[PDB]
Image (cartoon, coloured by chain):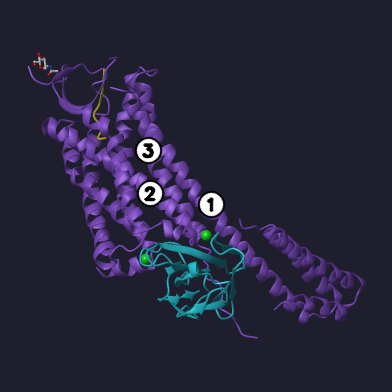
Amino acid sequence: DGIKRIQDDCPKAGRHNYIFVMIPTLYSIIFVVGIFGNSLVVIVIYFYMKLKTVASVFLLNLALADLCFLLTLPLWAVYTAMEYRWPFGNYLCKIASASVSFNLYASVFLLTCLSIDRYLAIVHPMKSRLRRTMLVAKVTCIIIWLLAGLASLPAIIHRNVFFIENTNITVCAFHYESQNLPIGLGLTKNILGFLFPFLIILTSYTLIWKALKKAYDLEDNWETLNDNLKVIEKADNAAQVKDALTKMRAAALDAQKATPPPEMKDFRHGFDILVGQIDDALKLANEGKVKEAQAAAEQLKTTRAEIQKNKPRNDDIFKIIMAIVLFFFFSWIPHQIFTFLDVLIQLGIIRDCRIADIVDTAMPITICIAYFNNCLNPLFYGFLGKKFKRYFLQL
Amino acid sequence: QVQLQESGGGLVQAGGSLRLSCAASGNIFDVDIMGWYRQAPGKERELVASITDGGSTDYADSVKGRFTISRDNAKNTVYLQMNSLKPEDTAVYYCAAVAYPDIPTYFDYDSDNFYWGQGTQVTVSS
Amino acid sequence: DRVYIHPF
Ligand SMILES: *[C@@H]1O[C@H](CO)[C@@H](O)[C@H](O)[C@H]1NC(C)=O
Ligand SMILES: [Cl-]
Ligand SMILES: [Cl-]
């Protein structure tokens, strides 16, 4: 005479005194830190910086998506605190789950576009500049909003308030009926919410890794030649000359490997001349002719009296790229595994309430690590900007 | 801020030649990549050419064979040798560059590590 | 019949 009455297979699954106490406490921390954290991000990025880059648009919408999810968070904290009892009705049930699902798909899709933007702004800054305008930045977002809504559309449909017959506990959840709701609901979160975005983000930063590694390896090969060439100028015997000429010959071969991305045949031929000029200098060092080999190595720098500006570069960028990929991986792979197991329990192989408990006990644990590490995404991505860090520390 | 001083644009006969120089100022370190963009009246901006700090150039199909770009790493100045200036080359030629900070984390929400110039008008009369 | 009480 009202809502749908459901029989629960494993009613005592995930119900523990330590889950009802720790989970709402962590939700309050995520609520306090998330709101205080993300709100200040949207201030600096809009009122202090006026949104003039494409990443600035992605960063603002990334923080607003987290802010929308945090507003519905007080509903889930008390929901867990009441031993999973939902009094908020069916209206807030369809909205709370949709808001959590929408913002989780939107935040991951936004991190995907941010990676594609960094790959374009680094490897091809000149060509991709005219394509990456401010209009495309706002158009990309409304495509993400529509995709995050369409992917979370089954969440607004199959999320009803149910009354368990054998426990008299009214809950808001998904009804995994025997047959006659799609099982692809849990799959979409695994492939569209993790697999597909991770393979695109990893490919972007890996291509940035290989692009920056080639640039720094080439920069260090020239540094290897110039530094060793100054050792010949201050050399004494033929042993100290051959030791430096042997290191320069390997550096010329390593620099011959780098190739961005007839023009490249001229690049490698320019180093075959370099290696060839090192061979003759090595021939004089093997015979024991120091002052003659010193002139052969000094004629090498004939192509080069004003000191020029040095190329700025950081060796710590690889720590950032690796941390960015791992911080996204190890923050969703706990929730993605226990969700994949749920798909096996949903309609398949697993028929045991003893292991269905470890799924419902560790699910809010994985939701907290997914929620806490995602609500800090716009903050830490923003700290990677020298201009953003200065304004944020002033507030 | 990194400013880009441009010079060499003016009214010139069709089929002649012109050289555009763009020097970078206010940059403590070297400039990563520099290039040239032109804005035709009533059109959108177009990439003319670009050159890497190592010497790799990339021209557009609009100026192949007639335009040649080079750079001086000592002066951080790029030259756009525009030979056989056709009346279609009449546009506002902007200078572009990519400059990274001292310890550069390749994230920039203020300028995106991309700096423009004032621009010079290059009018080609026939 | 399974009940998935979790937020997502
Ligand atoms: C649940 O309520 C029904 C009446 O609605 C009652 O018959 C049943 O015994 C109750 N069971 C429990 C476990 O409370
Ligand atoms: Cl490019
Ligand atoms: Cl910044």
User: Looking at the image, which is closer to me, A165 or A142?
Assistant: A142
Who comes first in sequence, dot 2 or dot 1?
A: 2
* Residue in the picture at 47% in, 78% down: B27
Q: Which residue appears farthest toward the top when viewing the image?
A: A179
Check the image and report above or below for A203 versus A384: above
Q: Position of residue A302 (x, y in %)?
A: 75, 78
Q: Is mark 1 within 8 Å of ligand 2?
A: no
Kind of residue indicated by mark 2: Leu
Q: Nearer the viewer, residue B88 or A45?
A: B88
Residue hosting label 1: A207
Q: Which chain is purple?
A: A
Q: Position of residue A94 (x, y in %)?
A: 18, 33
What is the C-alpha distance between the residues marked 2 and 3? Answer: 11 Å
Task: Name the kind of residue labelled 1 in the image.
Answer: Leu
Which residue is at a point 75% across and 68% down the rendered structure image?
A248
Element type where label 1 sits in the image: helix
Quadrant of the image occupied by residue A240: bottom right
The residue where tag 3 is placed is A193
**A166 relative to B8 in the view: left or right:** left
